[PDB]
Image: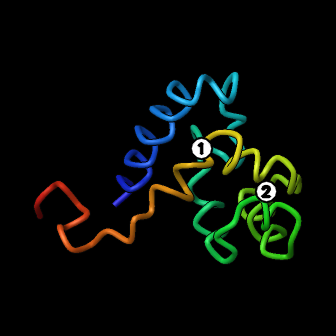
Amino acid sequence: NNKQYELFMKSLIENCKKRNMPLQSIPEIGNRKINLFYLYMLVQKFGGADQVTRTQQWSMVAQRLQISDYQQLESIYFRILLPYERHMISQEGIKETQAKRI
């Protein structure tokens, strides 16, 4: 528990530095250090960030972390790690997602 975040973490950054710094520095929209995956978990409702950036499913995203800035939201999904949250899915599971054993 509390490790899931650290996972996406290394994922996003690798993207920010690989996507040519698509963000000067994560706007830590939520509370602790970064959390673009949580509110993101909600965007799943739409799946299409740019589609959810201006929908009802966003009022929950944006509000989830307590940002009330739907625009900053997809800035989270799209601007900090679009390809990831969206294209990193792959619907994995047929090879054990969790690399660490229990």
Residue 23 vs residue 18, the one in the foreground: 18
Position above or below: 50 against 81: below
The x and y percentages for residue 53 are 82, 60
Q: Specify whether 68 is left or right of 92.
A: right
Residue beneath the point at 72% across and 35% down? 27
Please count the marks in the image: 2
Q: Specify whether 18 is left or right of 52.
A: left
Q: Specify whether 47 is left or right of 50.
A: left
The x and y percentages for residue 98 are 23, 61
Q: What secondary structure is marked by label 1?
A: helix
Find disc 2 in the rendering and name its residue: 66
Find disc 1 in the rendering and name its residue: 81
**Marks 2 and 1, how far apart at CA:** 20 Å
Residue beneath the point at 65% across and 61% down? 39
Residue beneath the point at 58% across and 66% down? 41
Residue beneath the point at 62% across and 23% down? 21
Residue 45 vs residue 36, the one in the foreground: 45
Which disc number belongs to residue 98?
none
